Length: 193
Length: 193
Ligand SMILES: [K+]
Ligand SMILES: [K+]
Ligand SMILES: [K+]
Ligand SMILES: [K+]
Image (cartoon, rainbow over the protein chains, first blue to last red):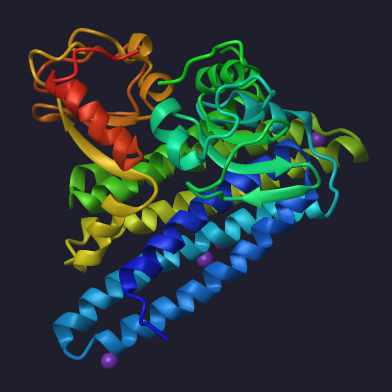
């Protein structure tokens, strides 16, 4: 069983907690319980990652100096853990079926950074391309945090994920970026970058 | 004194806490105490905003139904507050001069989403343009969270902020997006979008 490094564990924690906050907001925006449940499942992966980060960290330190540096890692993971649980608190609200004040969804759609639902049409130039090749974050400023494909959800999709007509992309980015990607997705704009 | 709405207060809280997390990571990456101090100052603005959100919220509810909806707002603000304090915990570490384990900066530079320092040269096409007109988030995928201009920091700059040669932009985005913006900033790529 090949050994993982502290860094790769740390990186997954950081990447994961950020995905969780995005999905938490998405679950509130669309009042979607499945997205919310994904957030709680990720919250457990965070706890697991944190445990491994601690195991690795602890064993790594053998002298005072090393110990002090290992502690800085644990402190940041602790802060990450707090952000994780906060995201979990947001998801719980959706899972409880609570009736949300209307300003909540509006706020999510009107902040500097929003969550948007993007329908992919048959004639769009992104149909048949992987996220890896499209690399939407880089090329559009829109970060794809999930895709609804029929009755299934693909959360935090790879660079290997290939887009199909009918897919519904859940993206994060500025309003303008989102509206832009929609036109592309609609096929109205037959060019990316 | 014109009345603010719950939404605008809520929006500033959400926008602000996100800026705080970005700056927290930036203060760790560059071991920069001034950025870290900005994070603690923002943490106070969050508390203030939260207080106002509570005042407004409380007064708004007059019946059981309204009260239940107002509570959903307070619950989310509470989660935001937890993310705020977590960001503050990260900044405290930098302010304490703690010696960071090397994996920390590497992790910030190697995650899915990174923090990058971008030098603007005299010959770059963005010199003399406002963020509003460049709207880098939309047009490049790079989110500018701050600018170091000489001996001064401008945090969370407006759409009215005009870029100058010599400015050092602090951006958030994918590695590829960041490297791209650097070429533009270098003037090597005389075209944006
Ligand atoms: K040890
Ligand atoms: K805590
Ligand atoms: K009342
Ligand atoms: K707490």
